[PDB]
DNA sequence: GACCACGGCGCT
DNA sequence: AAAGCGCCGTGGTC
């Protein structure tokens, strides 16, 4: 029930391929095949074979499409059963799993993969039968978006290598001064990178009171938060906090990034994973460029390393208070929609409160602090943690939480409805109908249940913002190609583009408009836009 | 070398 | 009682 034919596969066939490694940009195409009707075609010389295809249909189409772009081809990605599955159940994140759940085994033979892609698409496509809403998301968002992600990955972003190279030597020296002090304070050297060794030193050798425990092993935590609480109990704590910062940045960004520069491009190429999140957001792997530093001074110094090619400019666009505007539209809370209809900003307002300064005195750093608070409280943070963090009394934190929700009466009602329906149906959905199954909504253990609920009511808000960003990327991409501009990165509610200096303004202008008008809501969407030679200056 | 579980921590 | 991610050392394998 599956014969073999000479390479030349008929049009519309599903491809199957094997890579030396999972990164499309660094991978060696080991094998390539195709499956159609009831037979399979294997290419004797894979690279040569790529030229024959007109489209990539099958598991991980975008990835082969990326490698294709890397070789000068324009093979756009088409149907991909992974996208259908992801839409049926966001827990379908890997081929291994999707193949086992929907009909087969993910092997290492290209032929078998092409055959697998075909039968999988057939079964999954049959399951979406009637799911008009998921069908809309597939054809109007996911499938086209895959093409967008391909170009983004293949294009990559420029990095100032010698800059980070020198930054490394500089920080290494500061790390040395910090570890050296810590050791003097402890009275003896030990591996500071080891949480276990630091536990003993802090809680046994020194007489510092433990503040909390780790989740799976119950050890006394040495988290930055636990360290905050002990900042004044001993001189060694501040030191460890700075060591933690520097080494985190150094080992995670400063040193690894310069070594990931592809030779044929001289740019960094990240993976944009389309089926890896339970809410519908994307993620970046290998170089995960969705978590590049930005808070601290050294963090900012690192972001300054992402630069535009000579003669071009980076254009950074970011939705304003994105998830709050979504909540207003989902909850229907008129007081909250009025906030936006009146051009207000909850982050600036919370910041004003936090630091005891008039709005107009809040800086971007203070406002950034307030966002974690606003979203922390919205999504479930406890009075206890809130009081701890802000460093205020329990009652003062308990009051803020009360006022917050009392101020937007409809939000809690919406939350409550999202859960009831979630309990009955077994899943929750976004504005466009993206679904996430949350069975634990009925666990008989409060601990597990309430955690399940927090995950449950957050999905529609985070997911909807995701649908929006993806939709916008799909509408924006073609407009950019015609203007000679390129899309480089996506950071959940942010886009980083690269445009020739003579068009950077028109591009910024166009992107902003495209994004703000993506899908009109009961509240306007505002996009902040910036232009500059490096990512930091862009925003 | 190649992986994994964890505690941590960078970003949204 | 914030949610969603991926990556880095440490320990401990294999
Ligand atoms: C920063 C942050 C954001 N989010 C979500 C909600 C929002 C979305 C995007 O993040 P941000 O862009 O940082 O926040 P924002 O869109 O609310 O506002 P702006 O950029 O204008 O400052 O991610 C959280 O759930 N937790 C967080 O800590
Ligand atoms: Mg934003
Ligand atoms: Mg953002």
Image: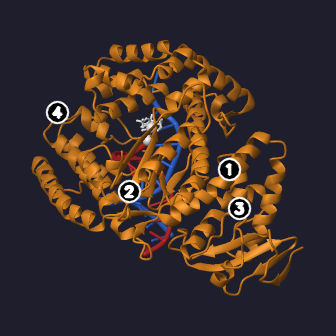
Chain colours: A orange, B red, C blue
Q: Mark 3 — residue?
A: A78
Identify the residue at horizontal 71%, vertical 68% (top origin): A55
Mark 3 or mark 2: which comes first in sequence?
3
Q: Mark 2 — residue?
A: A313
C-alpha separation, residue under disc 3 versus residue under disc 1: 15 Å
Q: Mark 4 — residue?
A: A233
The one of A310 and C1 positioned closer to us in this rendering: A310
Provide the secondary structure element on which disc 3 rests.
Answer: loop
Mark 3 or mark 1: which comes first in sequence?
3
Provide the secondary structure element on which disc 4 rests.
Answer: loop
C-alpha separation, residue under disc 1 versus residue under disc 4: 49 Å
Position of A528 compared to A277: left or right? left
Provide the secondary structure element on which disc 2 rests.
Answer: strand
Chain letter of the residue beneath label 4 in the structure image? A
Q: Nearer the viewer, mark 1 or mark 4?
A: 1
Q: Mark 1 — residue?
A: A86
Identify the residue at horizontal 39%, vertical 71% (top origin): A266
Mark 2 or mark 1: which comes first in sequence?
1
Chain letter of the residue beneath label 2 in the structure image? A
> Residue A17 shows which numbered tag?
none
Q: Are marks 2 and 1 on the same chain?
A: yes
Q: Nearer the viewer, mark 3 or mark 2?
A: 2
Q: Nearer the viewer, mark 2 or mark 1?
A: 2
Quadrant assignment for the N terminus of chain A: bottom right
Residue A188 position in % (x across, y down) = 13, 54
Say which quarter of the image contains residue A385. top left
């Amino acid at each position: 029930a599956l014969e073999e034919a000479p390479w030349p596969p008929p049009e519309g066939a599903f491809v199957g391929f094997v890579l030396s490694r999972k990164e499309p940009m660094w991978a060696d195409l080991l094998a390539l095949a195709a499956a159609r009707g009831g037979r399979v075609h294997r290419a004797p010389e894979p690279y040569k074979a790529l030229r024959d295809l007109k489209e990539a249909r099958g598991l991980l189409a975008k990835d082969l499409s990326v490698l294709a772009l890397r070789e000068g081809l324009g093979l756009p990605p088409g149907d991909d059963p992974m996208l259908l599955a992801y839409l049926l159940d966001p827990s379908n994140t890997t081929p291994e799993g999707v193949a086992r759940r929907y009909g087969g085994e993910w092997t290492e033979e290209a032929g078998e993969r092409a055959a697998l892609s075909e039968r999988l698409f057939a079964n999954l496509w049959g399951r979406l039968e009637g799911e008009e809403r998921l069908l809309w998301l597939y054809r109007e968002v996911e499938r086209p978006l895959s093409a967008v992600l391909a170009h983004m990955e293949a294009t990559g972003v420029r990095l100032d290598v010698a800059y980070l190279r020198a930054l490394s030597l500089e920080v290494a020296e500061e790390i040395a001064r910090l570890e050296a002090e810590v050791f003097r304070l402890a009275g003896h050297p030990f591996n500071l990178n080891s949480r276990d060794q630091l536990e003993r030193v802090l809680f046994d050798e020194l007489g510092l009171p433990a503040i909390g425990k780790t989740e799976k092993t119950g050890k006394r935590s040495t988290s930055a938060a636990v360290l905050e609480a002990l900042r004044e109990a001993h001189p060694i704590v501040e030191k460890i906090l700075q060591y933690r910062e520097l080494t985190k940045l150094k080992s995670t960004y400063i040193d690894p990034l310069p070594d990931l520069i592809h030779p044929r491009t001289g740019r960094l190429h990240t993976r944009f994973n389309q089926t890896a999140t339970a809410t519908g957001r994307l993620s970046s792997s290998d170089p995960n460029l969705q978590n590049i530093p930005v808070r601290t001074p050294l963090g900012q110094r690192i972001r300054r390393a992402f630069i535009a090619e000579e003669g071009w400019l980076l254009v950074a666009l970011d939705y304003s208070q994105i998830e709050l505007r979504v909540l207003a539209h989902l909850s229907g809370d008129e007081n909250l929609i009025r906030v936006f209809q009146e051009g207000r900003d909850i982050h600036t307002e919370t910041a004003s409160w936090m630091f005891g300064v008039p709005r107009e005195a809040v800086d971007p750093l203070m406002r950034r602090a307030a966002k974690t608070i606003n979203f922390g409280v919205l999504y479930g943070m406890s009075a206890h943690r809130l009081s701890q963090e802000l460093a205020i009394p329990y009652e003062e934190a308990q009051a803020f939480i009360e006022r917050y929700f009392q101020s937007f009466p409809k939000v809690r009602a919406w939350i409550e409805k999202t859960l009831e329906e979630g309990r009955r149906r077994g899943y929750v959905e976004t504005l466009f109908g993206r679904r996430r199954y949350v069975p634990d909504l009925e666990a008989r253990v409060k601990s597990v249940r309430e955690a399940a609920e927090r995950m449950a009511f957050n999905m529609p808000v985070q997911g909807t913002a995701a649908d929006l960003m993806k939709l916008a990327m799909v509408k924006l991409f073609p407009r950019l190609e015609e203007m000679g501009a390129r899309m480089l990165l996506q950071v959940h509610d942010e886009l980083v583009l690269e445009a020739p200096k003579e068009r950077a303004e028109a591009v910024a202008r166009l992107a902003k408009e495209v994004m703000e008008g993506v899908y009109p809501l009961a509240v306007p969407l505002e996009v902040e836009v910036g232009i500059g030679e490096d990512w930091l200056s862009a925003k």
